[PDB]
Length: 118
Length: 11
Ligand SMILES: [Zn+2]
Ligand SMILES: [Zn+2]
Image (cartoon, protein in one colour):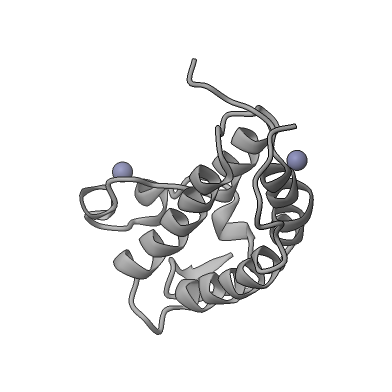
């Protein structure tokens, strides 16, 4: 498969960042792929071409899918951005996403800046 | 859970 490895930043995103978000109270809509049919969301997969969720990010971290932490960071920002693009700014889902991203940025701010392979 | 999907939650 694709090249994967373990780095200090990937371990931090797993054992610190993902841990804080997975148990969060606002996390339940993000722990699995959006099911636009079950939720009745029109044109979701025509608008969202790259769906992403914390469940997929979690499995990728736990299976050493990522080569660098920047790939994992991109997946987190894809998940947030997809929420802001499809949903209306005052929908409940956007406020929950903004709250989760607030904790995300707070924990990522303390991430070790130098990425080293372990 | 959702009252109205994405728009308004119940919990
Ligand atoms: Zn679909
Ligand atoms: Zn884990």
